[PDB]
Length: 266
Image (cartoon, rainbow, N blue to C red; front, side, top):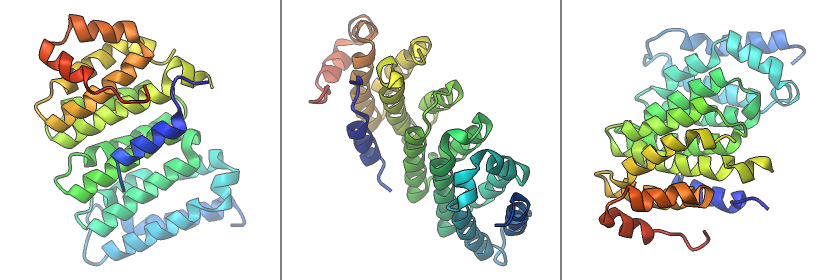
């Protein structure tokens, strides 16, 4: 079997983050739906049309062409600059429009998943991660959920996405740092040598160790608690390295607290 039971672990991760006749005709329809997004300025006069048009775009990605021909569909959404234009709505101060756009991107990730080039996954990850720092609670929490779902949906290991996740540990507001402890856990679950077969992480252990040390000594109690639990996932993947952190790198304070955070199934 695999080191981790992904079916079980994913349900836990998600609980941390509660919520055409031709391709040319498709492209023309996309260009017409994106027209109200072409202006930088959201106005009283275009925000409802932007929201309504995202609903129609969501209907389009549920269609047969993205299911049957994701590769050429990806070429189309690149050419019409779908992600950049959708980012004008994720940045809206209007809650319903920003949330509608975030859920659209979540559904796009789900449906196209590993058919998306890294450049587009990177684009979407940055939109999500930056909203983790929103002072608006429903925004950061929705972005958190979308990021966890992204990691579950994307089955290829990308160093770029691991580094974007890692560097959240340096953000000043608590939520990205807390999210980062869950993201690290997700990477350990899915992409350790055992789970991946059914090395990606070996060369990233230096970052993992810094990531753990920072979170476990975080000023915020929720980040410390989350990172102490993630430490035991690291211990399950690389016990020699984790033991060295526990004895050769932690104070007796953080050591005892970390030892009391073992989950009952690991």
